[PDB]
Image (spheres, coloured by chain):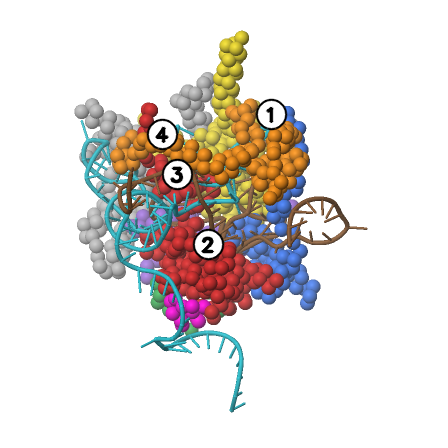
Chain colours: B yellow, C blue, D red, E purple, F orange, G green, I brown, J cyan
RNA sequence: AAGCUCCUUCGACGAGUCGAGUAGUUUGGGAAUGCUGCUCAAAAUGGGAGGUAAAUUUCUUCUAAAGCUAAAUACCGGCCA
RNA sequence: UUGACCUCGGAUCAGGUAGGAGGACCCGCUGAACUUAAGCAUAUCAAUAAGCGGAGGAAAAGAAACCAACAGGGAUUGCC
């Protein structure tokens, strides 16, 4: 039993996409999550993962809609930031 | 409109992907891989080898298809692939060898099912007139028309055709994007490898005048027949040796 | 191969197994009137009368299993329509 | 020549006439016992081509067998289980052949032809008195009926190498070490 | 006569969904505002909440 | 190659001279029932099928109906006078027909046929 | 008239039809079987 | 038998127009390479060189196609939030990954 | 009663069985090697298995779904030698 | 009212037959594990052992919906 991080295993394209892959041994450019909206969406998945199984179907849906609304508000802020960057 | 196409210029193409009776499991796997490539493709079951070859045209009219990809198998070992426009167009017969399907765990590449590929052709495809006919039949069969409702909206794989020997080598590759060092493309092989040996090109649909003949094709059955003739020739040389040696002893 | 002079053989009565008997074709046509039509043959009959000849051959393959069987079955049922409008 | 008309009628089992008759007879057989005797064959064309005669010594028996499976698959057909149950019921008779008559969603129906080997009409008549010989006791138990020959793979060709001349016999011949006197 | 390559009324692919999502499970989109992408490359938004 | 139980399936042929005596007494027995007749039926001369054995020739099962007629032997009389008849085989060439007609003629020349009862 | 799906087998036909697995043409065509016209 | 006039007439009866002045690249998505790739392969039996020539030939087609498609506004990059059916299943991709772990573990445990 | 011959006359050949789909088992044998269950369910110049790149499925060879039949083969038991 | 035919019954009716044993060899059904792969799970053991049914002096198979590609062979079985 050894870690996949230590072995030089290539990333494989699955239903979950690989995306753009950064080269090994070079600068993996840091993206910051200082924004409160970007802080809320990460917080929604942490609280959802720890809570686990809920018997209620409605409360199970509200646990997912909180994550969905957090993603939408963050995306609107990022698009407004992208528009402000395009103006500048 | 019932073409399942949303485009300003509609390139209406339907391909009928069809297998013969005596195909192998490897031949069936290659059909399964190529049919997953084609959103405008319909799979078809075992075709009677005792039927007539132009009954494929009556078959493709029924399924409303203007292209036929026919997998014809001989002796339970060999594969022949046919490409044809259905009513009147040209028809080419290949001999398919060196098959490696998607299930082989040495490829490491994957792509979207039904996405529109980039067709990589070779310079020899535009020089030789018979390779120009094959290229257009390859562009019709593996086209994946632009506004097709069963297609996928992003591009992640390239289908390549290469003329190296007197044969056509077919490869798939995955467009993998890598961030540039202060984006670039890497290719990872996905799917089917198969070598096509052009045997004949017909003017009719599955029969008609012959426009091109290979005249260099060594069939698999000619290799088998040469081995059996060599086995019998070895035995006959033994009998002629014994007949000569007995005649020498009687002298 | 070797040069051996060929000779023509008598026609084999087993090679006449391909049936051309006028009496058997009489019996098959008379029984078809008496027996009637299968449930799936009624679907083919209705589709051929409505003009959906393509749908008829697809349905009859899915019931029989072969293009040769689907082609013949639509051809016998086509001649039943032809002879029924002649009697009527 | 009524039997040629009957042969063509049995080809069209899904037609209006045959499906109506097979419906009302399936209900009638379920009202009766699982194994019972038929006075006459319900398919006289089929019985006659399988070797039935209207002589004293020939009887016809009807039988149901529950269809389905044991995911394990039985190596003999349901016709074979139908033949063995009739032969146990009529221990003095010999099973000659059997044929399909009806089919339900729960039962398969068969009719079995039996020959009495002690009836004088059978014994004096050649071309049937081979069944009087003691080598033909319980042919359905040993797989000598028509469905038995199909299940044991007794067909000529390169597609039945392991099953011609017996599967266990051919396996045994291929797995003995033959040692001669001068090796 | 040339074949018109159109889908007939009885065809298996006569009606194609707009989602362009295959036989994958739909639990991949559980935490997302959108559900799939159409053929043009723009995501399909979830309708509303009952 | 002894992964199975070969010890319970092993055949030793110590009856090799015993079965030779049994086979020779079986040949003597059918020479006593058929005393002036041969103990074997006459068999045609055929060519071996494959290309390895085209040049060589061997005895076949029975004479064809056509070569039996050309030699003057009726069908229903040939099994009664010791000639094997094969209804499956075909002549397919004049060379196979001529060799068997000559063979049947040579058998006729050497035959003594007894006048019924 | 109210159609109530109680049996699990009618649910199976409902799951096939509502998904893009069996069409309206396939359900009508396969209803012409031996249990039909009785 | 090589009927050069017949093959061209067979082409023109089934040929749809591929011109940069007439039709966009999104219509056809086919690129013809400049080199013949036979010059890149001296020996057919050389598996490593022959596969590198085929990998190379489709590499310019991907680069030429990507430049042309981005010029016309057609989306190219798959987004990270696009989950869809692929040609090889996730079960097959799992065996590919487990095979890669096995050779990676075997090479390093050899050095251990 | 029977064999042959000739012919301006005729010449009937086995269906819930082949076949297609699927599951299990089996084989050196996914042209599924065979077998069995379930669903659908045939044909009449027909059907089955092969040969063939040779230009279209051309050619070759047999008739399945009824039945009988001695010998050459086996034999730790039976009556003996 | 009487008489046919069909189906179904009764009788210590007249005459018959089956069961059990044996099972070395034979025809089917059902069906393991130890072992090997220095562990083990595909595989192998093995389409074996154990279990169930059915015959004879032999049983079974058997007169091509066969082999073949030949200048052709010609039911089955067994040996090399």
- Please state which of the two labelled residues, at mark 3 or mark 4, is closer to the viewer: 4
Residue at the location (62% across, 51% down)?
C19
Q: Which residues are magenta?
A: D27-38
Tell me the SS state at disc 3. loop
* 3D distance between C-alphas at marks 2 and 3: 71 Å
Q: Which residue is mark 4?
A: F17
Q: Is residue I74 above or below residue B217?
A: below
10 Å crowding of disc 3: few (<14), some (14-19), many (20+):
many
C-alpha span from label 3 to label 4: 75 Å
In this rendering, the label closer to the viewer, 3 or 1: 1
Q: What chain letter is assigned to the residue under label 3?
A: B
The reply to whether label 3 and label 1 mark residues of one chain is no
Between the C-alphas of marks 2 and 4, the distance is: 38 Å
* Residue C30, picture quadrant: bottom right
What is the x, y in percent for residue D42?
Answer: 49, 66
Q: Residue at x 58, y 43 (%)?
A: B51
């Amino acid at each position: 039993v050894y870690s996949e991080k230590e072995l030089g295993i290539p990333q494989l394209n699955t239903v979950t996409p690989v995306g753009v892959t950064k080269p090994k041994g070079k600068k993996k450019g840091k993206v910051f999550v200082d924004d409160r909206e970007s802080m809320n969406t990460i917080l929604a998945m942490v609280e959802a993962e720890k809570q686990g199984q809920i018997e209620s179907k409605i409360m199970r849906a509200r646990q997912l809609e909180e994550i969905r609304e957090a993603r939408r508000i963050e995306a609107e802020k990022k698009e407004a930031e992208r528009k402000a960057l395009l103006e500048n | 409109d019932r073409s399942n196409i949303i485009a300003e210029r509609k390139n209406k193409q339907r391909v009928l992907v069809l297998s013969s009776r005596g195909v192998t499991y490897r031949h069936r796997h290659l059909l399964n891989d190529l049919a997953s490539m084609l959103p405008h493709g319909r799979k078809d079951a075992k075709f009677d080898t005792k039927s007539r070859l132009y009954e494929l045209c009556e078959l493709a009219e029924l399924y409303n298809c203007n292209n036929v990809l026919f997998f014809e198998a001989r002796k339970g070992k060999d594969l022949y692939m046919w490409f044809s426009k259905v009513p009147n167009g040209p028809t080419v017969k290949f001999y398919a060898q060196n098959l490696h399907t998607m299930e082989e765990l040495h490829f490491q590449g994957n792509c979207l099912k039904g996405s529109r590929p980039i067709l990589s052709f070779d310079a020899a495809f535009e020089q030789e007139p018979y390779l120009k006919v094959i290229k257009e039949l390859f562009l019709h069969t593996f086209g994946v028309p632009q506004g097709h409702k069963k297609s996928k909206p992003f591009i992640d794989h390239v289908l390549s055709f290469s003329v190296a020997d007197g044969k056509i080598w077919v490869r798939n590759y995955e467009i993998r994007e890598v961030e540039k060092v202060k984006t670039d493309i890497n290719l990872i092989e996905i799917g089917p490898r198969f070598v096509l040996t052009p045997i004949i090109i017909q003017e009719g649909s599955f029969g008609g005048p012959i426009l091109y003949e290979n005249k260099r094709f060594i069939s698999p059955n000619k290799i088998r027949a040469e081995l059996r003739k060599a086995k019998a020739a070895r035995h006959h040389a033994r009998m002629e040796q014994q007949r000569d040696l007995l005649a020498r002893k009687r002298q | 191969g070797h040069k051996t002079t060929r000779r023509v053989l008598k026609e084999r009565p087993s090679r006449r197994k391909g049936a051309q008997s006028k009496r058997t074709q009489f019996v098959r046509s008379l029984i078809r009137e008496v027996a009637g039509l299968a449930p799936y043959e009624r679907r083919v009959i209705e589709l051929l009368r409505n003009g959906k000849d393509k749908r008829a051959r697809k349905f009859s393959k899915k019931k029989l299993g072969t293009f040769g069987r689907a082609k013949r079955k639509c051809e016998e049922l086509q001649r039943i329509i032809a002879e029924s409008r002649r009697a009527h | 020549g009524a039997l040629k008309y009957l042969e063509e009628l049995s080809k069209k089992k899904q037609s209006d006439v045959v499906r109506f008759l097979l419906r009302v007879r399936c209900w009638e057989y379920r009202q009766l016992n699982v194994i019972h005797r038929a006075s006459r064959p319900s398919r006289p064309d089929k019985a006659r081509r399988l070797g039935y005669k209207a002589k004293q010594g020939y009887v016809i028996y009807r039988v149901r067998v529950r269809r389905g499976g044991r995911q394990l698959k039985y190596q003999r057909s349901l016709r074979a289980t139908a033949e063995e149950r009739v032969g146990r019921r009529c221990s003095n008779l010999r099973v000659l052949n059997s044929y399909w008559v009806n089919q339900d969603s729960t039962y398969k129906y068969y009719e079995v032809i039996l020959v009495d080997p002690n009836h004088k009409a059978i014994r004096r008549d050649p071309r049937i008195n081979w069944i009087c010989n003691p080598v033909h006791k319980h042919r359905e138990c040993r797989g000598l009926t028509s469905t038995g020959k199909k299940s044991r793979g007794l067909n000529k060709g390169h597609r039945f190498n392991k099953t011609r001349a017996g599967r266990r016999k051919t396996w045994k011949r291929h797995n003995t070490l033959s040692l001669w006197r001068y090796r | 006569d040339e074949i018109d390559p159109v889908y007939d009324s009885d065809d298996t692919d006569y009606n194609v969904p707009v989602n362009t999502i295959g036989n994958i499970p739909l639990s991949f989109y559980d935490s997302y505002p959108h559900i799939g992408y159409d053929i043009n490359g723009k995501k399909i938004m979830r309708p509303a909440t009952g | 190659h002894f992964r199975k139980h070969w010890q319970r399936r092993v055949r030793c042929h110590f009856d090799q001279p015993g079965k030779k005596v049994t086979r020779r007494l079986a040949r003597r027995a059918k020479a006593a029932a058929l005393a002036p007749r041969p103990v074997d039926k006459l068999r045609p001369i055929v060519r071996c099928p494959t290309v390895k054995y085209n040049r060589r020739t061997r005895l076949g099962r029975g004479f064809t109906l056509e070569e039996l007629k050309a030699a003057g032997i009726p069908r229903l009389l040939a099994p009664t006078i010791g000639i094997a008849v094969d209804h499956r085989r075909k002549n397919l060439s004049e060379e196979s027909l001529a060799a068997n007609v000559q063979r049947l003629k040579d058998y006729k020349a050497r035959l003594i046929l007894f006048p019924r009862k | 008239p109210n159609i109530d799906i109680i049996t699990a087998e009618a649910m199976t036909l409902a799951h096939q039809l509502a998904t893009g697995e069996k069409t309206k043409a396939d359900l009508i065509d396969e209803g012409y079987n031996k249990y039909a016209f009785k | 038998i090589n009927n050069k006039e017949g093959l061209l007439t067979a082409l023109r009866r089934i040929q749809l127009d591929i011109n940069p002045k007439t039709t966009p690249f999104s219509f056809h998505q086919s690129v013809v390479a400049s080199k013949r790739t036979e010059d890149s392969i001296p020996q057919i039996e050389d598996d490593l060189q022959r596969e590198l020539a085929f990998m190379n030939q489709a590499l310019e087609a991907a680069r030429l196609g990507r430049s042309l498609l981005r010029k016309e506004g057609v989306p190219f990059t798959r987004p990270t939030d696009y989950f869809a059916e692929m040609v090889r299943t996730d079960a097959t991709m799992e065996k590919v990954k487990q095979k890669l772990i096995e050779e990676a573990t075997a090479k390093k445990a050899a050095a251990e």
